[PDB]
Image (cartoon, coloured by chain):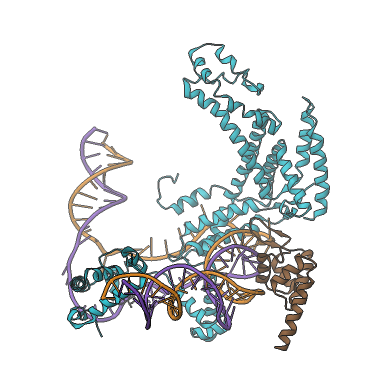
Chain colours: A cyan, B brown, C orange, D purple
DNA sequence: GCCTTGACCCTCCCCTAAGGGGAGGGTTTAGATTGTGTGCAGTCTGACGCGGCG
DNA sequence: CGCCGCGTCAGACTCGTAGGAATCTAAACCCTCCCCTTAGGGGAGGGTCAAGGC
């Protein structure tokens, strides 16, 4: 056994990946058949709940007047043109209505099963079928969460036996007939929850609407949903066997992308995501091999992840493709001319203007490491030569402080009103500068008078008696 | 029929169809909810032909909207005719 | 001089009709393909922790 | 359990100028969103110019 011998996650992955053998042309077909039988079982278990079929026939009468098209409702039929769907929808509606009234109780299990097997014929688009199964999951999980809030409160009270709290709770479904039997033992635990016997009502009386909103029994709903779970675990275990058998295909494709910015296991994992999508989308009834379809999705995922995350500064996919196209045009022009082309002629063989190609050539460059050795030494690196350009020079800070002092000096040599409106008009020793109207309203004076005051104060400061300190803070 | 096929059937740009859908002059027969893809139908071509017939007479777009959504608009064709002769004099 | 007043004036931002142009984002794509792929190294000497033998 | 060879880890000079590293790589569709096009119009916000009134 090779366990504990290597550190490489590539070797560990290849080691655990090679323990699944490749499928034949026949192995892919019956794995795909297992997937489609799992999904068919999920659908025939969905058919027991009626409102999903009601929503689907709502969708069809919306297709009738074209609020939508049935090309988005069904992908085809198995025993898309819109005339056969009329036949199948009519025969399905004639089944749903003939099931709706027949309620009894042994007779009620003939029509539901034949409607299930006649609803099996519709191979829906994934969106509608997923909507139906998620709708049923929400119905069953809210019903289930009040089902276990029934026991949530029973744990809120005291010690919790529910080994035999389930004895006659099954089947009554209308009232507290099962609830009265709990105090019939008169053990202390059977005390507690009973004084909460009123507060429990709106849980199991909210059942009062839902058993009138679903039509079928609590365990009937729960068990068609557990049959849905069995069907989807069959379809999910069969999808896992098709992904696990085809990981060599992903490595086979991913080895051709190995040095474009992403590492080999990164490419393998992105291609594995593409392969899982391919398994979800594959159709074996087209007669093609799984490799033929799956290569498209694996290559899509790998190239998309290279466009997404191979670069520090991310370039969008449209510019990534412009760069790739420019590069292969440059390769052709370098081969056919023996000389690296200039952007002028590189813009004439391409369809693009020259100023567009110049920025495309300036746009595709990867950052240098600041641990790059300069001089190819190991003592001085590129980061040692890069300067903080946001630092204020200490002579500039000292000039700023001297200028604050000088304007403080000249503003002390003005009237208190003029120095105030001139410290307020500008942001001097305030956090914000003000407009003529704000300075005026603070003084309860007009805008134009404040303009006059500040213009006069500026004219005073223009005189060389008050200006020779400040004129030193100017340049050529 | 997607917008690219309809733009080639109609011999008009795609952005023209986008504008006509935005203003409400020519609305696609079915818009795909998730993608947003506009799909068109022969009954949309019968209306784009009317749009083109009116737009070749120099009618403004809003005049075309008023003419195709509200009937008995013979005062608008007279306004456009008088404006055309005035522009001819000018 | 202090203070209003009515008339002007500035820049800046958003709007015009009918789309053009482009950026940046999604989606699929069905002959068949099913295990990577490089080096490189002329250090020595302590010193510590551990399988494996006794 | 005690000891011996093996696997592993951690250390090993500061001035000038040169000075990096250099491979490899979809396409056709659709969408929304943003800016752009005349020749200026309209308005908000903020200033400015002469009149005088005390
Ligand atoms: C800040 C530093 C001054 C010291 C200047 C002077 C010489 C410049 C380098 C060289 O030009 C080579 C190379 C050019 C690439 O274009 C960008 C990277 C390199 C390493 C440059 C980095 C940086 O710009 C240097 C170190």
Q: Position of residue A428 (x, y in %)?
A: 26, 68
Q: Position of residue A254 (x, y in %)?
A: 53, 60
> Which residue is nearer to you in this view: A17 or B21?
B21
Q: Is residue A22 above or below residue A223?
A: below
Q: Is residue A376 visible?
A: no
Q: Is residue A460 above or below residue B28?
A: below
Query: Which quadrant of the figure shows ligand 1?
Result: bottom left
Q: Is residue A206 visible?
A: yes
Quadrant (top left, top right, bottom left, bottom right) of the N terminus of chain A: top left
> Which residue is nearer to you in this view: A287 or C10?
C10
**Image quarter of residue A43:** top right
Question: As drawn, is A141 to the left or to the right of A111?
Answer: left
Question: As drawn, is C49 to the left or to the right of A117?
Answer: left
Q: Is residue A338 above or below residue A146?
A: below
Q: Position of residue A422 (x, y in %)?
A: 27, 71
Q: What is the tally of numbered marks visible in this picture?
A: 0
Quadrant (top left, top right, bottom left, bottom right) of the C terminus of chain A: bottom left
> Which residue is nearer to you in this view: A148 or A77?
A148
Residue at 23% over, 79% down: A460
Residue at 20% over, 80% down: A467
Question: As drawn, is A3 to the left or to the right of A171?
Answer: left
């Amino acid at each position: 056994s090779e366990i504990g011998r290597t550190t490489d996650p590539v070797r560990m992955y290849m080691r655990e990946m090679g323990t699944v053998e490749l499928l034949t042309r026949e192995g892919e077909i019956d794995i795909a058949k297992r997937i489609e039988d799992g999904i068919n079982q999920v659908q025939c278990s969905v058919a027991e709940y009626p409102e999903a079929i009601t929503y689907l026939l709502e969708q069809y009468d919306r297709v009738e007047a074209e609020e939508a098209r049935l090309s988005d409702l069904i992908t085809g039929f198995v025993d898309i043109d819109p005339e056969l769907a009329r036949e199948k929808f009519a025969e399905l509606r004639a089944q749903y209505v003939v099931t709706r009234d027949t309620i009894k109780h042994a007779t009620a299990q003939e029509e539901i099963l034949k409607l299930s097997e006649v609803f099996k014929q519709f191979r829906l688009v994934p969106k509608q079928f997923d909507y139906l199964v998620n709708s049923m999951r929400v119905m069953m999980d809210r019903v289930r969460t009040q089902e276990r809030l029934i026991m949530k409160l029973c744990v809120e009270q005291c010690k919790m036996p529910k080994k035999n709290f389930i004895t006659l709770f099954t089947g009554n479904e209308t009232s507290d007939t099962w609830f009265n039997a709990a105090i019939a033992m008169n053990k202390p635990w059977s005390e507690k929850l009973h004084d909460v016997s009123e507060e429990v009502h709106r849980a199991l009386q909210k059942l009062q609407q839902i058993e009138e909103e679903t039509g079928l029994t609590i365990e009937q709903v729960k068990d068609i949903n557990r049959r849905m779970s069995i069907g989807e675990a069959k379809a999910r275990r069969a999808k896992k066997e098709m992904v696990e058998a085809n990981l060599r295909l992903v490595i086979s494709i991913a080895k051709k992308y190995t040095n474009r910015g992403l590492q080999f296991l990164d490419l393998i994992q992105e291609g594995n995501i593409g392969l899982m999508k391919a398994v979800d989308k594959f159709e074996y009834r087209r007669g093609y091999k799984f490799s033929t379809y799956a290569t498209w999705w694996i290559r899509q995922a790998i190239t998309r992840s290279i466009a997404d995350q191979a670069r520090t500064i991310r370039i969008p996919v449209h510019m990534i493709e412009t760069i790739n196209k420019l590069n292969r045009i440059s390769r052709q022009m370098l081969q056919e001319m023996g000389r690296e082309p200039t952007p002028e002629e590189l813009a004439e063989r391409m369809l693009m203007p020259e100023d567009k190609i110049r920025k495309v050539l300036k746009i595709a460059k990867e950052p240098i490491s600041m641990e790059t050795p300069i001089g190819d030494d190991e003592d001085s690196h590129l980061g040692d030569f890069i300067e903080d350009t946001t630092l204020e020079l200490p002579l500039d800070s000292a000039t700023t402080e001297s200028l604050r002092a000088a304007t403080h000096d000249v503003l002390a040599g003005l009237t208190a009103r003029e120095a105030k409106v001139l410290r307020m008009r500008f942001g001097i020793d305030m956090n914000t500068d003000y407009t003529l109207e704000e300075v005026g309203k603070q003084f309860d004076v007009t805008r134009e008078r404040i303009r006059q005051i500040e213009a006069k104060a500026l004219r005073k400061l223009r005189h060389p008696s008050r200006s020779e300190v400040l004129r030193s803070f100017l340049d050529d | 029929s997607q917008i690219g096929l309809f733009s080639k059937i109609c011999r008009v740009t795609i952005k023209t169809l986008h504008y006509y859908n935005k203003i409400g002059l020519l609305v696609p027969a079915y818009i795909n909810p998730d993608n947003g893809y506009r799909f068109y139908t022969s009954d949309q071509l019968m209306k784009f032909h009317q749009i083109a017939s009116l737009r070749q007479l120099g009618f403004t777009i809003t005049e075309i909207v008023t003419l195709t959504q509200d009937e008995n608009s013979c005062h608008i064709i007279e306004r456009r005719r008088l404006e055309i002769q005035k522009q001819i004099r000018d």
